Amino acid sequence: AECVSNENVEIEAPKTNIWTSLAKEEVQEVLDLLHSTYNITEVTKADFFSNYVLWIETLKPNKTEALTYLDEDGDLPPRNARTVVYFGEGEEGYFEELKVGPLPVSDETTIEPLSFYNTNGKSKLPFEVGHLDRIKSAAKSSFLNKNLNTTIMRDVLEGLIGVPYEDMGCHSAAPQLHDPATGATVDYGTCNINTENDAENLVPTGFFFKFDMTGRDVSQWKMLEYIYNNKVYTSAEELYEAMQKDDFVTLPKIDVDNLDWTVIQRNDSAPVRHLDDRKSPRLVEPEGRRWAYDGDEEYFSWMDWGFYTSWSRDTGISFYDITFKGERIVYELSLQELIAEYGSDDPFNQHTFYSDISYGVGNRFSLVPGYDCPSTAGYFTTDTFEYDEFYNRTLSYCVFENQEDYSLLRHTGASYSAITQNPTLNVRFISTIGNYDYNFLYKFFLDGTLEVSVRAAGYIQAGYWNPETSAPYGLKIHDVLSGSFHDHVLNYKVDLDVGGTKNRASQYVMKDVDVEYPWAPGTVYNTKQIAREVFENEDFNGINWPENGQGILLIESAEETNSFGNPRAYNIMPGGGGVHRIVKNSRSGPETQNWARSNLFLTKHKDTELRSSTALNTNALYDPPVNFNAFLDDESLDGEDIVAWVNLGLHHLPNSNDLPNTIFSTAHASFMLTPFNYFDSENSRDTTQQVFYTYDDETEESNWEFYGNDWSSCGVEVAEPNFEDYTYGRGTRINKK
Amino acid sequence: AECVSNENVEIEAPKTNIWTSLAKEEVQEVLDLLHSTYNITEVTKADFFSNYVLWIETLKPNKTEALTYLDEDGDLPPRNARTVVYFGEGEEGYFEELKVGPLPVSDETTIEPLSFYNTNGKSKLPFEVGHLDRIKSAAKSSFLNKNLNTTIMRDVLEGLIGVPYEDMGCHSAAPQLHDPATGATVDYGTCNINTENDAENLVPTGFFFKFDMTGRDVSQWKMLEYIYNNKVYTSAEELYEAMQKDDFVTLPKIDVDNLDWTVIQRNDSAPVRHLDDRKSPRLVEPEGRRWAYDGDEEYFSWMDWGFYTSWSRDTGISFYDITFKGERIVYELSLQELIAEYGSDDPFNQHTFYSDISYGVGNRFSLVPGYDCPSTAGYFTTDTFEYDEFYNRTLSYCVFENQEDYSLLRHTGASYSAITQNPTLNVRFISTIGNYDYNFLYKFFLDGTLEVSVRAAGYIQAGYWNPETSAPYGLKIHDVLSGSFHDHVLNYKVDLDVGGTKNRASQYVMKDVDVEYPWAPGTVYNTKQIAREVFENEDFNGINWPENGQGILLIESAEETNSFGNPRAYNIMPGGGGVHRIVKNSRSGPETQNWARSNLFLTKHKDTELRSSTALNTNALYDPPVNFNAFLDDESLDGEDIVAWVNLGLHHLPNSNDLPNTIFSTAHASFMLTPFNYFDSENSRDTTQQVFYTYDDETEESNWEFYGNDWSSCGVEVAEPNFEDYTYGRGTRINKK
Ligand SMILES: *[C@@H]1O[C@H](CO)[C@@H](O[C@@H]2O[C@H](CO)[C@@H](O[C@@H]3O[C@H](CO)[C@@H](O)[C@H](O)[C@@H]3O)[C@H](O)[C@H]2NC(C)=O)[C@H](O)[C@H]1NC(C)=O
Ligand SMILES: *[C@@H]1O[C@H](CO)[C@@H](O[C@@H]2O[C@H](CO)[C@@H](O[C@@H]3O[C@H](CO)[C@@H](O)[C@H](O)[C@@H]3O)[C@H](O)[C@H]2NC(C)=O)[C@H](O)[C@H]1NC(C)=O
Ligand SMILES: *[C@@H]1O[C@H](CO)[C@@H](O)[C@H](O)[C@H]1NC(C)=O
Ligand SMILES: *[C@@H]1O[C@H](CO)[C@@H](O)[C@H](O)[C@H]1NC(C)=O
Ligand SMILES: *[C@@H]1O[C@H](CO)[C@@H](O)[C@H](O)[C@H]1NC(C)=O
Ligand SMILES: *[C@@H]1O[C@H](CO)[C@@H](O)[C@H](O)[C@H]1NC(C)=O
Ligand SMILES: *[C@@H]1O[C@H](CO)[C@@H](O)[C@H](O)[C@H]1NC(C)=O
Ligand SMILES: *[C@@H]1O[C@H](CO)[C@@H](O)[C@H](O)[C@H]1NC(C)=O
Ligand SMILES: *[C@@H]1O[C@H](CO)[C@@H](O)[C@H](O)[C@H]1NC(C)=O
Ligand SMILES: *[C@@H]1O[C@H](CO)[C@@H](O)[C@H](O)[C@H]1NC(C)=O
Ligand SMILES: [Ca+2]
Ligand SMILES: [Ca+2]
Ligand SMILES: [Ca+2]
Ligand SMILES: [Ca+2]
Ligand SMILES: [Cl-]
Ligand SMILES: [Cl-]
Ligand SMILES: [Cl-]
Ligand SMILES: [Cl-]
Ligand SMILES: [Cl-]
Ligand SMILES: [Cl-]
Ligand SMILES: [Cl-]
Ligand SMILES: [Cl-]
Ligand SMILES: [Cl-]
Ligand SMILES: [Cl-]
Ligand SMILES: [Cu+2]
Ligand SMILES: [Cu+2]
Ligand SMILES: [Mg+2]
Ligand SMILES: [Mg+2]
Ligand SMILES: [Mg+2]
Ligand SMILES: [Mg+2]
Ligand SMILES: [Mg+2]
Ligand SMILES: [Mg+2]
Ligand SMILES: [Mg+2]
Ligand SMILES: [Mg+2]
Ligand SMILES: [Mg+2]
Ligand SMILES: [Mg+2]
């Protein structure tokens, strides 16, 4: 017979999602007010001397006002926007962050400089250290074409590289290099062979350059150097003349006629593996979906968990008010930043230290149904605003229930077997940022554990292989290609509030010790002990996971205990990828990413310490809007609202197993938040997704208790995914405007 | 319409499984020959002065003869049995290992002392350090009853504990403590309250004792001490008299009337979570099974992988001749040992250092269909022989194809999206050894990566909570219960043969370094580099995973390279649980478990270094059959057949989340073996389980390429698991005898 079908369930959220992105109408009201207050130019007509709007987004509520609303019948917090506007109308240009609110627009609405979350106390970001925005990108591109497409440079480039200028693409290293001592801003760059399949990163040419881009007048910008085979030339003419001499060394050129090694998808001439003409397995829901949601509030419930989601252009998804069995465990869980920091012999890769939130993690592409998420997933639409357009992104994140490949627990003994299944709620989004594809997963378990993970895939940023200098910095993975060495590091703000806001952070340290026991006087034993140590103060050094795993890190309630006197706690448990930066002192990130140097940091919660990086950090090398180290000022954590800033990372040394692409299976990092004396007992025991088998010794009869789950054979339709809902591109745009 | 069904596929193995367990007929021939050669007593009639047979199993072939057979058209290696026989007919008793072969029995068959794989050079294990076999267990049990069930001790026990002798169970700590300097063998013990649900480990009484069990004449065995509240009494009478004094302290007694906190299975009075009245998700195979097997040879194929399995009483499953795309990567992969080493204030837990292979990992229970493995799993029968009976164990291990919850790789760019699914082959067995349930998984990926993992669940071995002394060694997790601190450590023999047997082991060390580049003279940069270092010699210290993950460990072919000159290699990549023992010098395991002190060891392959522990190790504290450290003798590894002995572990400090049972989700350890320059490229690209989506900019049309996989909706039957095949117990026995 047919399996019993049930419909998807919707619920009403306990409260309003006060963290949600601005509605289209709210964005429009703000943009309209900006246009009536200032002389705003459309981005498509703008230059460095115009004013124009970049960003308009929710300025999220402060925590005390949010908690009063959620927990104590408080007023809705004010609805405010953060906007970022470039002002070029003055003697000097700058970006300024402005607060617009409250909303909706009324006679109470104002526009004010906004800086409370910037540790440097400034609303204004100087032009020299400005955002690499559409206007600056276009200016740089035009400048490079002006220099590289001369009669002489066309000849130089074709001579060295083997293809004409039209067949390559030249571009600039990030971040830019502004020197506050001299005022100069310089930048390096390289060229890569053009491909039809987005594989430019696998065909770097080894031709480099350096330019001065100081000031808002591009007529004063100048090429400083051309660099090739580790030699520096101070003009096109010098390099051209050097190339005419008999002693000139041209390094091996890329074979542009044979690029099949860069292609990801199956060669349909390839043999099929045995049985690969059968479809692989599918997850199904025989009795329908087991999580519920409020569509308007983006509030989700599953097996006694509840939470709200929010979306930003900078970072993608965040979670607020994460509750389990009716108690908040985490106020805010939010990815903060992702860096990719390269080491190299060459002046492009050695100057690459990406801030992915500067580019945007939340302004990318839809998920591919059936492949990126299981076919049983539900999909959600989010939005952003950039440069005069509201972007609606369908299939932006997905929610699905997995059946994990192992049971949650079991035991066999005393003539019974008791086994509990392990269904999990899963929230995923994937951000493809140029060459990289980052896969973010949040996995919730029946006992109250949550696992946060990331996997990376996509094309690597390789480098040109110069046998004389490249070997310390990468493996030779193709004829003229190095797998350039880099660190990925990701910061998560984990605002645990265990048994209320007032908490303590502690560690149980494990050690071997020699002891004598009262029951064997005089006999020394080498044994092992625990010792609880309280993290009394913010530690500038952060916390690194202990050698040989010899410690357990807790966030404890300051006052609440379980029935046996233990502080209610959650354990922050590292999984794979518990690594931080190798490099200590980067010229490409002196002060911009100071959270990335230890595994984790504990701080006192502050509304002014909203975020560990900003989209405005990356080029502001010495005076970024947020210098994370400002948070670390030795404050007591001993009965305080604590935030853990937890890092995941990978030291990536690409090899053959990264061509044509890196794989997600071995590029993985995760951590868990797991109850530790948070209850009196383990709290999955109430699930019905378990079996109790008993055997009677006398009667020789077995009994199976399935707790209302009928495992009898039944028929289902294995449904086609919603492929028709997937359209390529970075969201549907509506110009405002 | 209905999904297209296909039948399970069977294949013929390339060769015979020369590692397989003895057939019933082979065991019978050996037992018959032992009975005709020696005076053998049935185990049920045996004592310490009898001779009797314990074990009869395959003595696996040596490696060179195996490889000649597999690869070079060699003869089948000789078919031999290892037997272990207790001989008590002499002046002193001992166990002896004997080789019986070749088989089948003929005039060529002999019986010889067997010791080549014992580093101590002995076939004979003295009685004092003997196996804790059925005969010795029975003698100890009888001795304890003789002492503890006297009129005086019945009164002492009821007075201190609160229930009569009939309502408790008293038992001995493992290992025993034999002192070679004096010849004495002693042992500690405790008592636990009897339960109906195998939860005795949650109700330890805090009553301890110590006895001398030296020699084969039990009439000379003597109780030495009773220990209670950290006080030592040298007789029952002394303790009884102390208990009559007004100043005697009786510690708080267990509440035996309220033990519901020990119960695993659902309380059907408990509320149901929202939507838990719907069945959780199921994995299905819409087009049938995609792995094949040879049922007689226990040879398995999946997506270009091949391997044979073997089963032993000591360790469970092993893998031989693991091939990927027609090349052997691993000759032998075999779990070797699992230890559980406790630290405590009390003389039971402090003297607990289990060797789980002494008890047997491969002589346990069947898997529960649908719960222990997915419903799409296939199940396999294995066998053992112990104490006159051949045991056939159905549902002993399972094989299934998972769909992992994340794709293997993807990329979006240049108007396409390319995503590859991540189906994996999975081989599981579960060994429930008393209180512990160990879940072993071997997971194979499309690119040639394999992941080895373990998860633990079941009841903890807790201890009595004495407020005066217990706190350094555990948390108070119930009214009179400590979560005793312990290490789990597991050893795997990983005989990688990368591009042949002759290999090198290397590490790429990662470090930050200050450098000056030729293209910026005089400017110092702090960057990062790699350096390849060869492990030239066996290192007595072993290898511990590097701080901050700053290294990659390889097994390289000595001679074979890929097309870019890199040695073909596999990377041994740690996942979670990359920990080793905390304790350094245990009185309960001085020389018996010397592999457990570092994360991994590399040695030169030897047939005499078959195994890192034995079932005969645990009580032989100073002179075990195998002392692992004997393998570490500074031999060159620089172009040699290398074996990696890889450890997984957990430092377990039980908390509330371990009552009533530990959970598998957070008690996890794993490592991966992943290709590293082993090919020229990443080798999943030929799978059909991928999609290539393209978008045409001009025509505004999308195209989907599914490589022959039809995702159209189709009907399937979701089948009932084979629950009828699950019978409780540790295998069906046939007495031989
Ligand atoms: C959320 O909490 C933040 C941080 O406590 C609040 O920040 C405060 O915002 C006000 C403006 O609304 C700032 O006042 C301004 O200060 C400048 C500089 O002295 C002064 O010139 C202006 O006239 C104005 O008074 C205030 O400095 C700032 N506090 C901090 C510590 O930076 C914010 O108001 C809170 N948000 C909401 C919605 O309540
Ligand atoms: C597999 O390899 C092992 C290790 O190389 C071989 O072990 C050898 O086994 C023979 C017995 O079959 C041992 O010979 C005996 O030595 C004793 C002691 O000196 C002697 O008294 C006996 O008369 C006999 O010669 C030999 O010592 C042992 N080698 C080592 C290094 O321990 C084993 O034979 C191989 N198995 C197969 C099936 O070929
Ligand atoms: C607005 O700025 C533009 C130049 O960006 C200028 O031409 C125009 O006069 C300004 N508008 C007003 C009303 O002054
Ligand atoms: C580069 O110069 C060539 C001729 O010298 C011209 O045809 C082409 O349009 C130029 N490219 C760009 C992008 O300006
Ligand atoms: C496809 O396979 C053919 C034949 O093996 C090979 O020559 C070619 O390089 C492959 N093409 C691509 C695009 O991968
Ligand atoms: C965003 O997309 C959703 C789903 O298609 C739709 O309901 C909503 O109206 C869209 N918003 C706008 C203003 O386009
Ligand atoms: C075998 O041993 C038993 C004692 O275990 C003894 O009674 C018997 O005489 C022995 N058999 C022979 C044939 O000597
Ligand atoms: C213990 O002694 C009691 C009486 O003193 C007796 O009834 C019981 O059978 C004894 N138990 C055992 C296991 O010998
Ligand atoms: C079952 O639930 C009842 C009511 O909550 C409780 O009193 C009892 O202790 C539970 N029993 C078991 C066996 O867990
Ligand atoms: C072991 O069990 C399998 C499967 O039930 C069966 O085919 C085989 O005959 C059994 N072996 C013996 C000798 O009982
Ligand atoms: Ca907090
Ligand atoms: Ca602080
Ligand atoms: Ca080897
Ligand atoms: Ca050696
Ligand atoms: Cl300012
Ligand atoms: Cl090339
Ligand atoms: Cl949906
Ligand atoms: Cl302590
Ligand atoms: Cl700066
Ligand atoms: Cl011997
Ligand atoms: Cl109790
Ligand atoms: Cl089966
Ligand atoms: Cl090197
Ligand atoms: Cl010994
Ligand atoms: Cu990478
Ligand atoms: Cu444990
Ligand atoms: Mg909205
Ligand atoms: Mg009011
Ligand atoms: Mg208002
Ligand atoms: Mg509503
Ligand atoms: Mg506060
Ligand atoms: Mg067999
Ligand atoms: Mg012959
Ligand atoms: Mg023969
Ligand atoms: Mg056959
Ligand atoms: Mg050899």
Image (cartoon, coloured by chain):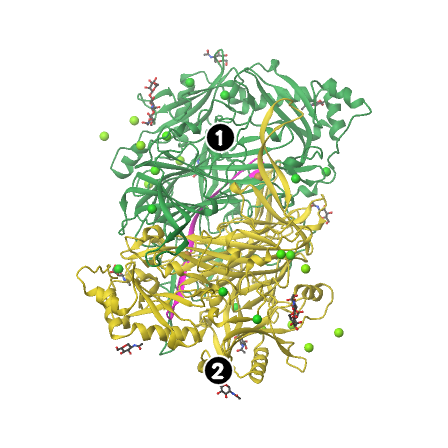
Chain colours: A green, B yellow
Answer yes or no: disc 2 within 8 Å of ligand 7: no
**Amino acid tagged 1:** Gln
Residue B634 position in % (x across, y down): 63, 52
In screen coordinates, is A407 left or right of B262? right
Who's the residue at 45% across and 83% down the image?
B45
**Relative to B609, does residue B84 appear above or below in the rendering?**
below
Q: Quadrant of residue B185?
A: bottom left
Q: Is residue A287 visible?
A: no
Query: Which one is closest to the eye, mark 2 or mark 1?
Result: 2
Specify the farthest residue to the front: B182
Q: Residue furthest left?
A: B246
The chain ID associated with circle 1 is A
User: Which residue is located at x 23 percent, y 70 percent?
Assistant: B155
| Amino acid type assigned to the residue bearing label 2 in the image | Glu
Residue A57 position, x and y percent, is 42, 29
Which residue is tagged 1? A593
Instruction: Give B100 or A519, whichever is nearer the viewer.
Output: A519
Residue A423 belongs to magenta span: yes
Q: Quadrant of residue B550?
A: top right
Q: Nearer the viewer, residue B207 or A565?
A: B207
Magenta residues span A409-436
The x and y percentages for residue A589 are 52, 27
**Residue B42, label in figure:** 2
Q: Residues within 10 Å of mark 2 (few under 14, many from 20)?
A: some
- Most prominent secondary structure in the magenta stretch? strand
Q: Nearer the viewer, residue B60 or B41?
A: B41
